[PDB]
Length: 159
Length: 159
Image (cartoon, rainbow over all chains, first blue to last red; front, side, top):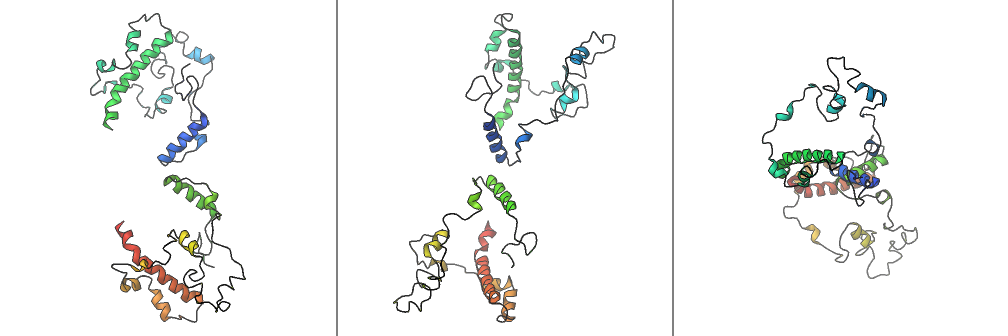
């Protein structure tokens, strides 16, 4: 039920032409050519699209379990075509073996993390079973978000 | 025939929707609002439209040789509605006979004057008479423009 973003309402999505006003004001602030079709209407520079058929069929490993490898592992990171991941995330798609995660000067401490949103830390010290399955998965999502948040926080303070 | 601003060619005057683009761009750049007709037509507030009768009669002072003072002298300066002059020139219409426009410490020297636009000195020593009345009157007009130009250029230079 929770919208990713809201205005005055708590469940639905904010008003369309108010967003048109938003994008108009902002692209006139940064002095850029706004065109409304090119953000509100559909482009064709889009993500992959599937059936039920191959989606269940090809991503099942046991139908292809004779193989030395299953493509779900490497070139499909979690059912994503790999360039459709990295190009849309503005990356040169040319490793298949992304190991940039250890590039972290000063990984932030969790004692600073557990200050804000500590109820999440309570929920996994609550009956972790007693919550719905999407709930604690979203909670771990939020913890990853808070980690990235504190990670990127010093430049936000810097500027 | 020559427009005060040429367009693509010398003879042609520029195109309108190009100026609509100009207004749209500069006004969303200079952060000023813009409703379109408000800069593409006559306002309600314009200079007065005259007749033939009084415009050839009230200003013809042979009709009014009777008078102690003639109307064009003070308040109709060279056939000019006076507040239409000062308010459209953004000048206070209540002082009304100001004389401080002559003030210029370091007035524009004639040497730097006669250097720029040097054909004026020529066209005076050329056929200053047997050309059009538009010719030598426009020469005097260019003398006015050049006088303003030198008299007000160093602020542009400073800025």
